[PDB]
Amino acid sequence: HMLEIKDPLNYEVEPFTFQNQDGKNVSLESLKGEVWLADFIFTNCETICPPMTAHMTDLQKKLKAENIDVRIISFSVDPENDKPKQLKKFAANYPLSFDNWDFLTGYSQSEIEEFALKSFKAIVKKPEGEDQVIHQSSFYLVGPDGKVLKDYNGVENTPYDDIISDVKSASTLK
């Protein structure tokens, strides 16, 4: 045994309704039941170079097999300055497929705040990100209830299973 008997997570992402990069409305309603993948990023600074979305892009392939109605959601970090147009432009660089990939607006950080706080601690307002600034591109695997059950970090080094698990227990063992 090491980190106990592994790093089970249960990170409940509070349901809400969002608009995707198609201007199309989607809620957790459409995903709760399913094992849907999640991430969140900006693209505003950066030239495009590291394997940032590359992991997601690679997994988009696998997704065909997982498809059922699992979607890989990807919400905007600081959507006021970035905006879904930047995610679109970035998707025009990282050679990805909207195919079965819901890039979500979230809208103003006031809107994004409570959502991303509860869900992931991932707001931009008072904190800048004190972690999710430099080059993080962490996966979440969001379970059927809406609780996350695995993470990964793509570029390895800080897999985020371990951290989110530890935070899970430390919080109040969700």
Image (tube, rainbow, N blue to C red):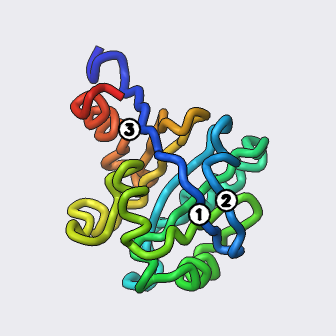
Of the two numbered discs 1 and 3 in the rendering, the one whose residue sits closer to the viewer? 1
Res 55 quadrant in image: bottom right
Q: Earlier in the sequence, mark 1 or mark 2?
A: 1
Instruction: Give the labeled residue for mark 3.
Output: 161
- Type of the residue with mark 3: Asp
Residue at image location 42% in from the left, 38% down from the top: 11
- Compared with 135, 114 (above or below) is above
Could you tell me if the residues under marks 1 and 2 are in contact, i.e. CB atoms within 8 Å?
A: yes
Q: Earlier in the sequence, mark 3 or mark 2?
A: 2
- Left or right: where 116 falls relative to 173: right
Disc 1/disc 3 C-alpha distance (Å):
26 Å
- Compared with 28, 73 (above or below) is below
Disc 1/disc 2 C-alpha distance (Å):
5 Å
Residue at image location 39% in from the left, 82% down from the top: 46
Residue 18 disc label: 1
Q: Secondary structure at mark 2?
A: strand
Q: Secondary structure at mark 1?
A: strand
Disc 3/disc 2 C-alpha distance (Å):
26 Å
The answer to which of 58 and 137 lies nearer the viewer is 137
Q: Quadrant of the N terminus?
A: top left
Residue at image location 41% in from the left, 31% down from the top: 9
Res 17 quadrant in image: bottom right
Could you tell me residue 57's position as x and y percent?
62, 61
Could you tell me residue 156's position as x and y percent?
38, 49
- Type of the residue with mark 2: Val
Q: Quadrant of the C terminus?
A: top left
The answer to which of 38 and 174 lies nearer the viewer is 174
- Type of the residue with mark 1: Phe
Residue 26 disc label: 2
